[PDB]
Image (spheres, coloured by chain):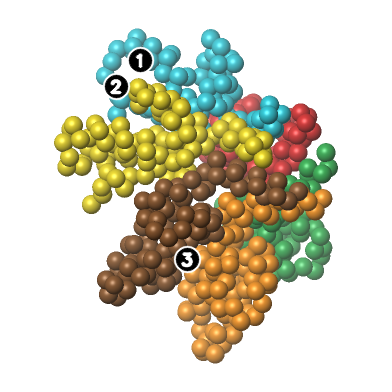
Chain colours: A cyan, B red, C green, D orange, E brown, F yellow
Amino acid sequence: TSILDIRQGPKEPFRDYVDRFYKTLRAEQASQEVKNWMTETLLVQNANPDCKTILKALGPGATLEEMMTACQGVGGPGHKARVLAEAMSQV
Amino acid sequence: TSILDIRQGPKEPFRDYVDRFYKTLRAEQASQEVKNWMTETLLVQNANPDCKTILKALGPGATLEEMMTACQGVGGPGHKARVLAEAMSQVT
Amino acid sequence: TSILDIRQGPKEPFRDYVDRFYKTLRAEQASQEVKNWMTETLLVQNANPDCKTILKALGPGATLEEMMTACQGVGGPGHKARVLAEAMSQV
Amino acid sequence: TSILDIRQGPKEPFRDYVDRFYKTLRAEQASQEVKNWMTETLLVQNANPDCKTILKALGPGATLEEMMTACQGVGGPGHKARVLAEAMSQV
Amino acid sequence: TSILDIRQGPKEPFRDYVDRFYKTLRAEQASQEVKNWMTETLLVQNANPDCKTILKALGPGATLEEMMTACQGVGGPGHKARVLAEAMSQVT
Amino acid sequence: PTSILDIRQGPKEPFRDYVDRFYKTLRAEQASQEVKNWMTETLLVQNANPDCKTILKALGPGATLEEMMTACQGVGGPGHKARVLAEAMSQV
């Protein structure tokens, strides 16, 4: 089990995935500075395309509490229809 | 386990999220006065965007009996379909 | 587990919700006359909007066998298609 | 547990509903003659609306293996598409 | 249980259904010859309509490796959408 | 026993999950390490379901694991389905 193998499933909630990332990062023998750097590059990189498109729109300086509120809609009745009703228009 | 970590899943029913919120609130090293203030602030802010839009429409003064009866359709056949319809009308 | 705390989930079938309602009602500490009054009022009130809209059409006098026969379509293919078409043709 | 309570869920496959009916039927206290009359009346009556409109179109005489083959499509990814298409053309 | 009662669920994958079929066939009390005749007739008849439509297009002489590879798309995003289209176009 | 040749991706299974089973199974196969590398290049990309295969077929040769898996973790998601469903109706 290595921190680099943790990826968000295609239908996994972002809350459930952020917990596995931290659950794993508590075992990987490394320095605190490294673990913080890990948290700053892998977390948003290894997210699924749905959450990734939303986390990029926020930009830098966003904390967990700011992402974890912007992604708890992914997979809800509002999202699936907002996206679905767009691909119809886009094509 | 902290009360601030309890969020409503994107597909979780509101009834289940309210249970965890209160299930987690009754074991917090907080005062009774604080736990009431927590209930009023955290409960509605940590709901997913589907329940929130519905709750934010009721306004202040709504009890759990009024909120939960208004959200138990979220994710159901009627609610899902209605949303999709208004998604084709707003964009066409 | 109070009796007033039993509600019908959004995706939960009616058969399953009624089972929990009675499972919990049998454990309540109260009199028989009260328990029957509970069933008459709470059972249809704590139901989700879909089963509720179909129950308010049967009206009063419907039995626990007429209701369940009227709601076991909720959440099925025939139901979902019927609910979706009616909404699309409205806007 | 009584044979008259067994009902097909709104999303339950038809194979898994016939399995519980007979699992329950073999336990009900009655004679074989009464159990054969239960099967002809209850089994089809307690089916959900989707697995019922199909059976009502075979008519009498169709055995179990004749029905189960007619109902194993309900809920498949080709059944919904068919039901959903007629609903639109009806409004 | 008896091999004649093994059917493919409406939402079950073909891969998962061929395992119970063979798992059951290895338990059915018959001769090894009657078992090959079972596999050649029942395995396809007891499949759900979605997979059956794909299998009856290939024809005779197709091996499990060819069938299983042709049905592991049933129930997927591309497959679902592909069926919902021909119906909509060949209807409304 | 399980043969590496029978590990196929379910019609509704995440690529991450199917990859893990492939490697969990390949670690046990009694082949030689030279035969296992050849297995990884042929079977893994061949025994995938049609939804992931069409995308891997686009990456082309020279694609590492970290590149494939990042390309497939969207399959089965809202953005994916809506995009695949939108072209089906457009192609017909």
State the SS at label 2: loop
Q: Position of residue F36 (x, y in %)?
A: 22, 35
Q: Inspect the image, locate mark 2, and give the three-letter code of the amino acid beneath it.
A: Glu
Chain bearing mark 1: A
State the SS at label 3: helix
Respond whether the residues carrying marks 3 and 2 are from the same subunit. no
Residue E88 shows up from this direction: yes
The residue under label 3 is E45
State the SS at label 1: helix
- For the point 47% across and 43% down, the residue is F12
- For the point 43% across and 13% down, the residue is A40
Q: Position of residue D49 (x, y in %)?
A: 67, 64
Question: Which is more toward the observer, A73 or E5?
Answer: E5
- For the point 70% across and 46% down, the residue is E89
In the image: residue E58, left or right of residue C6: left
In the image: residue F30, left or right of residue A35: left
Q: Inspect the image, locate mark 1, and give the three-letter code of the amino acid beneath it.
A: Lys
Question: Which is more toward the observer, F40 or D40?
Answer: F40
Could you classify mark 2 by the number of other residues whose Cα lies within 10 Å: few (under 14), some (14-19), or many (20 or more)? few
Chain bearing mark 2: A
